[PDB]
Amino acid sequence: AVSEWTEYKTADGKTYYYNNRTLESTFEKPQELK
Image 1 (cartoon, rainbow, N blue to C red):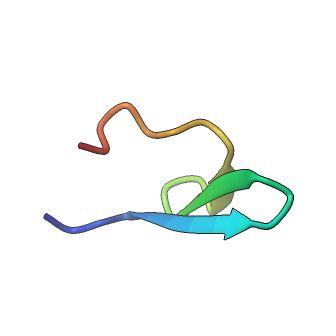
Image 2: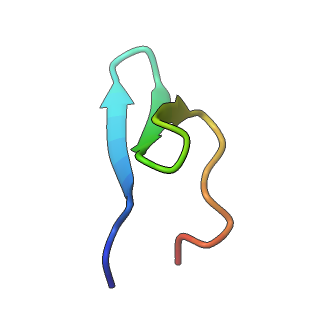
């Protein structure tokens, strides 16, 4: 499927998903991402 949620993981131990829906990197794992 098309991943509109991009996986960015910083060594700090934070996975921030960058999406063009809010133009925002969210630290909440997308509930639709499966």
